[PDB]
Image: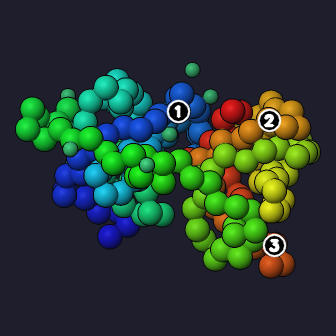
Amino acid sequence: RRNVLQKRPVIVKVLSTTKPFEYETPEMEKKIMFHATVATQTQFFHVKVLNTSLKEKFNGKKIIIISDYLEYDSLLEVNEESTVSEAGPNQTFEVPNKIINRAKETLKIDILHKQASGNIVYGVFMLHKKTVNQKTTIYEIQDDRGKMDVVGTGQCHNIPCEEGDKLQLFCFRLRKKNQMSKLISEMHSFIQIK
Ligand SMILES: [Br-]
Ligand SMILES: [K+]
Ligand SMILES: [K+]
Ligand SMILES: [K+]
Ligand SMILES: [K+]
Ligand SMILES: [K+]
Ligand SMILES: [K+]
């Protein structure tokens, strides 16, 4: 149910948030969002927060209840139609450290080269080389097992960084270049220099 608001509340610890950033809609309009990573006692979720008025609810000082969110791309979208509120005195919990650690893992690039087209990728990767073009930036990212291209457009075009900088990627689309994988920026994608 791609476009159906999920009523089933999800009750989560906020593990991390990004700064707010500007993103370009398909029609080239500018909107504001931030990314979040949240966890239950048994799983973690990446969360697109398109309603930046919620930033303080995601400050990670409190367990929160999210309802009327969208579910797709294995992630949660919290938008202007969503509700977020602090969990009650009886609804609080701690997240097992195994989940917190799993949430922050990055796949090796040889694994990404064998991954199916259409998957979503979040991860921290070292920059080998950057080429800025008219509307695209090719960020060549590398680990000890491989190298792959990151195609940045819109808010992901022409981000300042140097060889050896760690790029934190949010919500990239894996696509195939003749059996090699590439990571393609989409409307809600983000690059943070780490
Ligand atoms: Br609240
Ligand atoms: K800022
Ligand atoms: K920005
Ligand atoms: K985050
Ligand atoms: K507990
Ligand atoms: K552990
Ligand atoms: K898109």
Q: Is mark 1 within 8 Å of ligand 4?
A: yes
Judge left or right: residue 25 versus residue 174: left
Would you say residue 153 is visible in this rendering? no
Q: Are marks 2 and 1 in contact (CB under 8 Å)?
A: no
Secondary element at image label 1? loop
Mark found first going from the N terminus, 2 or 1: 1
Task: Quickly name the residue at label 1.
Answer: 18
Looking at the image, residue 26 sits to the left or right of residue 69; the answer is right
Q: Give amino acid for label 1.
A: Thr
Q: Nearer the observer, disc 2 or disc 3?
A: 2
How crowded is the residue under tag 3: few (<14 C-alpha within 10 Å), some, or many (20+)? some
Q: CA distance from mark 2 to mark 1?
A: 18 Å
Mark 2 lies on residue: 165
Q: Secondary structure at mark 3?
A: strand
- In this rendering, would 175 be left or right of 118? right
The label shown at residue 49 is: none
Q: Position of residue 134 (x, y in %)?
A: 88, 44
Residue 18, image x, y percentages: 53, 33
Tell which tag, 2 or 1, sits nearer the viewer: 2
